[PDB]
């Protein structure tokens, strides 16, 4: 590859990206031009490449590599619909992306066309004088954040931290020392009005001000009981919509002190000013709150977040609700990686297509693609690359015609192969448009003796689905190069699910039929083999985790999986005592299984959504007193 | 032994009790008399024994066996201070007392002098038409409760179910079906004013009405956020003291429909009407509430519960507070068995002495001794027998001069030997008068690599304390007869704690000193042996659990211990990886350990209180989303 017109910075960036893409032997003249986000023209090995914004050079090169495998003549012109496209990684659900993996992620985002990289850190960044904040969580040092940001800057990608300045601070506020307890209202919510809370928040911005970036998402989502705990005890009943504004104004003043411009999640305005306390509502704004908001709206960008709607109209409705408060809006979409071990790129594609229509219809300047890790971070950080390419394609081209070819240029895999990563969730009888259906997770963590999700299993279809999935994924692993770990992990999981999906039911059928030879088989052969496979899964999972994340947080998985293993040993031992005639009855097996949840009771399929480890694993108490 | 004056019922009861006590070959003439709770006179093999209330015969027999070992001549007269002395077993914290153990407990309570046996059941009794209420919890059927009660009736011991009609329903309200969710306010609290809530409660009393007893404790403690969840969203802001009264009225109306008389925990009146939301307060009663409350207080007995005070004076202050609301009061004291694996009979003794003074000074007629099982029910049900004998002696004699001798008649062990059961809690530098200090539990469940309670350990003291305790307990085990299991369990726990108390610290010390030999030894000898020892403990614990309780709830302990075991394996593997030179640092060990809590920071000792498994075991998230 011969380039003319590059700076040293750009030539060095390109050197890094040769680790992902193969530049052919051609001559490319490069310039900045406002004419297009990306333009590439020329033929017979001599090409002219222009970008509007510096970071767009890297997507241009991915396009160039792609189209030259196909043809000698190139006519590319792209007009991105969004001023900014960002990817936000969850670093608060136990999985803290390690620095080396943050660098890989940045490289890929740059090839895809993202302008912005973001980390969501509730308590997982260090604040001077707050030793419990992020303690044993692998909180990023200021230096690590600076290194990560500086790396992104190598590709003209900007960095935006997503923090919390109200709720979602559960891992911090649990620490039973006065310096932390005095900051609390209730649950995971900080105490509005308490000066020590504003000292903490000032501390958050002092840390962040060590970065170059002056753009921040301050959070403030899901503070459902705000003003109703220690706040209510100290101050009595207040208008909670005004309370939100008072808090918001204090935080904005602190941001201003450090020169930051803020975004925030939008949901609490709607929840606190709607009759049934929900996000998706047209709001009745009390006049005093309307006056307060009118002055605050000019100082903050509201982020409408929605990972769920299957149609443009549903989004547009919410955009119209938001316009009643502000026209300075951004949108946050979803790269589904928060439903256990296995992502849902398929569902992500479905909703992105529709969200992109709505966002364009409402002149949304910025889309933030979110990669949440709900309830323990058990899905791989790189599991959702197809979703990321999907949104990039939608911004730059408004279609997916180039999705797989650009994807294979950037990763070595076709997007279709990569999206087989979803397989543990893709039961055949599901419609593609319902969210959160996560058998990958609940089949895995379910008990043996007390299988409380058993009514949601359909062994005739599920067993061969999982078995075939494991074979499909082993084949993809062998051609996945450096992405192999992802597929190996999923293959082993599907192998486990193919038998575990009904082992609990088979134990009960054998018990009821008095088939003792079968119980003996299950206790002495199948369940010990099940433990061996789970330990193999745990090893693969640990390799995956340690490759992507800091070690901190893996401990919760160690605990969860060690518990599962011990519960399988209980199944073995209880069966043995019964077979030895030292029990008349196995009481666990005498209990009739009820539906776990009725959330999809009306549908013809049996699967469901169950995404809390502690209620998957047992009907007993385990965290409560 | 030969008796005259016995009914058939009494003759049958004494036959059963010969299983516990050794009646000497003497002649006893028995009659009821008003002259004393119990009197015994006579000599030379011929005795006259009177009792006031039928159940007191059985304590009288315990006393007779005791004194006849001392002497031929007998002069006994007792006047009990309390009309009723009850023991309440927690059957809601995962450990549901099996029917066989309920019968043993009743037999022992009879010999001690208790008039009343109680079971605390949040969701752990069956309600027709409510299939999720007690699901997979080992909830008692009506027939099991009837059997337990009829068995108590054999000894003229009455039965009082303790239930919940407001909060503490967490194991039920988690179930994600509409028929459960529609009953919810917030957290573990039912939705006041919802008719389906009142249908549920009617169901509760429908079940209980199948019993003979017409006395019930309806709960209503600790509903901290009542009115502030779904209640607030549906109904707006209301006077919460009035809300409580409205709910209470409804519940009492349901009780009246079935002929019940109610007791209730008193705390929410004080908490809702005090300015800081605390129990130990003389409260200003709002005017509208006083009207409502004065009516309600004539329909229910308030139970002042307090397990913590080391002085009469503090109890007296709270009695005075209560007396400004009602003179229809009972008192609840504590047999401390809710702080992990190991009871605190010693601390129970200390507070009982002072509480007994206060109850006597305030004319209290009924004392309920409570045996809570907080956060998984991991302490043995029979671990607190000394605390039970203590309260019986305080009622009947107003002193403990007879405590050890009556205890040994009743159990075969001196009370001093039995109370060694407490040892895993009895660190030598603790004063006797501070509650909740439970190294038994937190030393056990603490992580290895990330030992977040390490600052609370005092190895030079604690190590020989635990090792010596294990020997002491092994000796007592050998003379404990049918109670041996209790001491066997505790012996193995103390053996584990003597090394585990500082294994995390020694790993850190060897790591910093670069003592790779000690790291090897710890990885390859100590930690595998530790896992072996914990598996033995798990085996002993399981035998104890299955002897005393239903199998339901053991699963949570399997999970917890399974997870601990797996975390010890992680410590082994991380060290190995490091020893192999495939890591430059073990990041877990580079984190400086802070105090876990400042609760007892001002004291001379290092130990503390930490009684939530999920926060002992990890600093990561584990139940939150
Ligand atoms: C702003 C926002 O997205 N908040 C939460 C987020 O933390 C994560 O849990 C996500 C996926 O389930 O759901 C949202 O309710
Ligand atoms: C009425 C009552 O005693 N309520 C609770 C009880 O459930 C138990 O948890 C106990 C020991 O901690 O503490 C209490 O505050």
Image (cartoon, coloured by chain):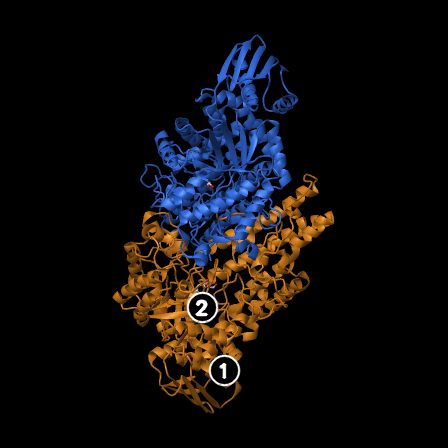
Chain colours: A orange, B blue
Chain letter, disc 2 residue: A
Q: Secondary structure at mark 2?
A: loop
Q: Nearer the viewer, residue A376 or B268?
A: B268
Mark 2 lies on residue: A281
Q: Which circle marks residue A313 in the picture?
A: none
Q: CA distance from mark 2 to mark 1?
A: 44 Å
Instruction: Say whether residue B551 is visible.
Output: no
Find residue A66 and name its label: 1
Instruction: Work out which residue is located at the far top of the displayed protein and give it.
Output: B44
The quarter of the picture showing ligand 2: top left
Left or right: B464 in relation to A421: left
Give me the chain letter of mark 1.
A
Q: SS class of the residue under badge 1?
A: helix
Residue located at (66% from left, 49% from top): A523
Marks 2,1: beta carbons within 8 A = no
Quarter of the image where the N terminus of chain B is located: top right
Q: Is residue A142 above or below residue B525?
A: below
- Between disc 2 and disc 1, whose residue precedes? 1
Image coords of residue B158 (percent x, y) = 56, 31
């Amino acid at each position: 590859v011969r380039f003319t017109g590059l700076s040293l910075k750009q030539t060095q960036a390109i050197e890094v990206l040769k680790g992902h893409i193969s530049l052919p032997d051609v001559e490319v003249a490069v310039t900045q031009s406002d004419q297009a986000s990306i333009s590439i023209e020329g033929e017979e090995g001599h090409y002219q490449l222009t970008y509007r914004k510096p970071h767009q050079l890297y997507r241009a090169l991915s396009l160039l590599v792609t189209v030259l495998a196909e043809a000698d003549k190139v006519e590319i012109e792209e007009q991105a619909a969004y001023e900014d496209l960002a990817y936000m990684v969850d670093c608060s659900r136990n999985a803290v992306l390690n620095v080396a993996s943050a660098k890989q992620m940045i490289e890929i985002l740059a090839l895809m066309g993202y302008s912005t990289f973001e980390l969501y850190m509730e308590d997982t960044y260090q604040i001077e004088g707050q030793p419990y904040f992020g303690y044993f969580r692998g909180a990023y040092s200021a230096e690590e954040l600076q290194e990560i940001e500086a790396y992104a800057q190598q590709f003209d990608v900007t960095f935006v931290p997503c923090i919390q300045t109200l709720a979602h601070l559960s891992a911090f506020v649990k620490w039973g020392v006065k310096e932390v307890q005095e900051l609390r209202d209730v649950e995971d919510i900080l105490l509005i009005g308490e000066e020590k809370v504003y000292d903490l928040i000032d501390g958050m911005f002092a840390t962040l001000s060590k970065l170059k970036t002056r753009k921040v998402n301050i959070g403030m989502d899901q503070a459902h009981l705000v003003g109703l705990g220690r706040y209510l005890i100290l101050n009595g009943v207040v208008d909670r919509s005004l309370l939100m504004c008072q808090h918001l104004e204090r935080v904005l003043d602190i941001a201003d002190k450090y020169g930051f411009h803020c975004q925030m999640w939008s949901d609490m305005f709607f929840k606190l000013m709607s009759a049934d306390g929900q996000y998706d509502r047209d709001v009745e704004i009390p006049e005093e709150t309307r006056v307060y908001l009118d002055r605050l709206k000019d100082r903050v960008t509201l982020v409408y977040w929605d990972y769920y709607q299957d149609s443009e109209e549903k989004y547009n409705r919410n955009f119209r609700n938001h316009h009643k408060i502000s026209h300075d809006l951004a949108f946050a979409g979803g790269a589904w990686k928060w439903i256990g071990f296995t992502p849902h790129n398929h569902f992500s594609r479905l909703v992105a297509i529709e969200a992109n229509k709505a966002c364009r219809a409402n002149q949304i300047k910025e889309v933030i693609v979110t990669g949440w890790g709900d309830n323990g971070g058990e899905t791989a950080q790189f599991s959702i690359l197809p979703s990321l390419q999907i949104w990039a394609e939608l911004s730059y081209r408004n279609d997916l015609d180039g999705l797989s070819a650009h994807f294979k240029t950037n990763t070595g895999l076709t997007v279709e192969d990569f999206m087989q990563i979803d397989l543990a969730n893709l039961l055949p009888d599901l419609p593609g448009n319902l969210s959160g259906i996560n058998p990958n997770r609940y089949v895995f963590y379910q008990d043996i003796l007390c299988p409380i999700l058993d009514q949601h299993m359909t062994p005739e279809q599920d067993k061969p689905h999982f078995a075939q999935a494991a074979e499909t994924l082993a084949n993809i692993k062998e051609k996945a190069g450096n992405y192999a770990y992802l597929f190996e992990t999923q293959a082993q999981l599907n192998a486990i699910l193919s038998s575990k999906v009904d082992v609990g039911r088979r134990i009960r059928q054998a018990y009821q039929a008095d088939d003792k030879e079968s119980l003996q088989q299950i206790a002495r052969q199948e369940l010990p083999e099940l433990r061996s496979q789970i330990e193999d899964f745990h090893a693969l999972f640990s390799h995956q985790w340690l490759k992507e994340n800091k070690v901190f947080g893996l401990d919760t998985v160690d605990i969860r999986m060690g518990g599962l293993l011990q519960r399988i040993k209980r199944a073995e031992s209880r069966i043995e005592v019964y077979l030895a005639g030292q029990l008349d009855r196995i009481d666990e097996l005498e209990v009739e299984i009820l539906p776990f949840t009725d959330f999809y009771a009306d549908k013809d399929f049996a699967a469901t959504t169950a995404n809390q480890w502690h209620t998957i694993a047992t009907a007993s108490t385990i965290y409560t007193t």
